[PDB]
Length: 165
Ligand code: NI
Ligand code: NI
Image 1: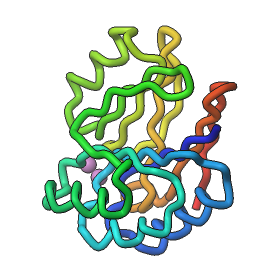
Image 2 (image 1 turned 90 degrees about the horizontal axis):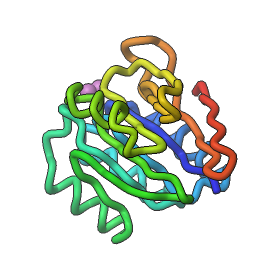
Image 3 (image 1 turned 120 degrees about the horizontal axis):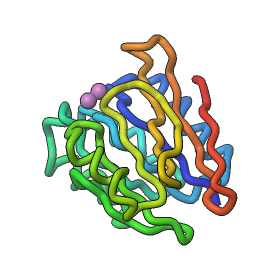
Image 4 (image 1 turned 90 degrees about the vertical axis):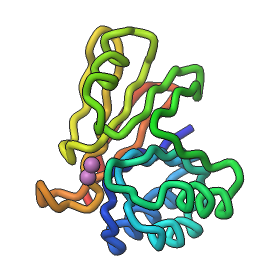
C-alpha cells in the first residue's frame, strides 16, 4: 500500500528513469504526478512504469489532449486533469500543480481533505496543518534547487519519506 509521488519532471529523462526504477523496486500501487512532464516523449518513458498513473496538468504542459491520450494508451486506468479530487486507502486526496495558489490554499484550509499534493514551486515540503497532510514531492528534475527528489507515502500508517535521486 505505497503511493509514489513526483512532480515537475521537466523532460529530465535520466531522473525520470531513476524515478521509474525506484517506484518499481517498491510496491507502489499507483504514482501521482503533478508537475509539468511537459513534452509528449516523457510519456513513452512511462510505459515502463508498473503502477497506474494519476497526473495533473502543469502550467508548462502544452500538449494537453495528446498527453491525456498517450497516458491512456499506456493504460486506460491512468487519469489527468487540472484538479484531481479522489479517495485512496480510506484517505481523501486533493491533487494539483501548485499552479493556482488560491485554489491550493482553499483545499488545505477547508478541511475537506486528508492529504493535499502539489508541485509547481519545485520546493519540496512535507508538513501538517489542521490534520491535513500537505505534500510537495519537490522537483524530479532538480533544476531550480539542484536537489532532485520524489517521494513515497504509506497509505495505512500515513508515513512519508523523500527520496533524493
Ligand atoms: Ni515546473
Ligand atoms: Ni510549474
